[PDB]
Image 1 (cartoon, rainbow over the protein chains, first blue to last red):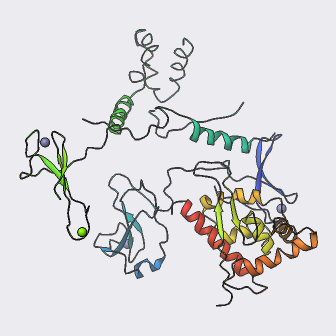
Image 2: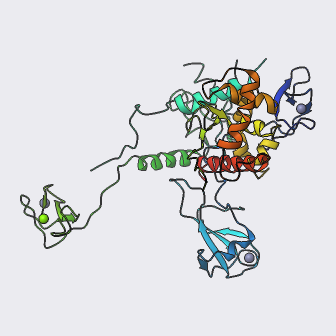
Image 3: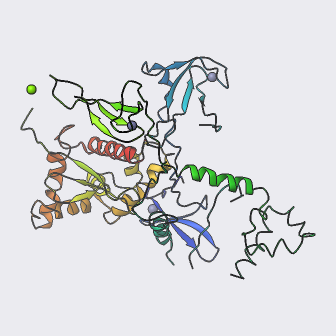
Length: 119
Length: 46
Length: 116
Length: 147
Ligand SMILES: [Mg+2]
Ligand SMILES: [Zn+2]
Ligand SMILES: [Zn+2]
Ligand SMILES: [Zn+2]
């Protein structure tokens, strides 16, 4: 989604349709502000989420002693130095796929041999 | 069923934003496709 | 128905288928017718037939009820079907002075019982 | 140490997983009803939405958590300034304690003495108690978003 606020109010924006020119706007319900929409998408639900998997990957991730290490060669820098964890999306369903974070290039690679990622 | 992505496009027949948010809740929560109500996880057994 | 158927277818065609448608043509018618028926678608548706037909199978699968798989010990016996194919699992039924109840189950004829 | 006010603050996510209008209200000590989070921030001094949202959600990117805050913003839309927020809090007693000057003066005291008594029970610490409430809403939503 990614929504905007009113400059002047800082209050949130409500969508208004410009019936005449068939176009979407964003009105402020505290002042007389109006701005045209960036995207046609107003609301996104998302039931089968993937946002949470690689959360809290601070560059300090290597400083956690609790995290386990592996000798897996990186797809980028080919470094056999990396820390690993499972999908941080705390759901029942969730697969046991592993996320490896490079102790040099910091690139996040997975063990998923069914699908190919970029997060 | 052939086409790569699986999509369903819906439209109604001033003020419509909230109306559609009700329609999507009805859709997910109240629309029964297959099966009998109260009957979940059906296992086959020999 | 027719318308538806027719338408649707127609528508378808447109778608893609165309081519186828164309063729138608041619064719026849027838185818248608057828367608119506179936338906046709597959047949118607292609080329879907495959997938659409294959997709049903995954659904068959998702319809069968988990199989409690369990071992059978060759030194444990049933009271009816007088056969050495029985499973067991122990629990702490009694206080810490007597320990281990051990429940049996004739994995073939279906009788269950305790050992103390 | 000191009297030990055993006032437990509950920050409630109304509506179930699959119910429309999932609002966030909070039960304040000595106040019968659960006030929608927004009004509390407004009564605190954090007046425009987004200034309020900044205290709750720390990542401007995270659309998922932000959509979850839109109902609250709608719930607190009625109250627009600090005063009207305190009156709304003051209306809901107590008992009620009838008189306009009286109820607005109350809400001041409750937020100072009974709301989040650790941190401070002093005066000018709205900023501290607002960011805390926002840290609480962040945690409430973080669990509801299955993270
Ligand atoms: Mg005894
Ligand atoms: Zn404005
Ligand atoms: Zn690397
Ligand atoms: Zn037996």
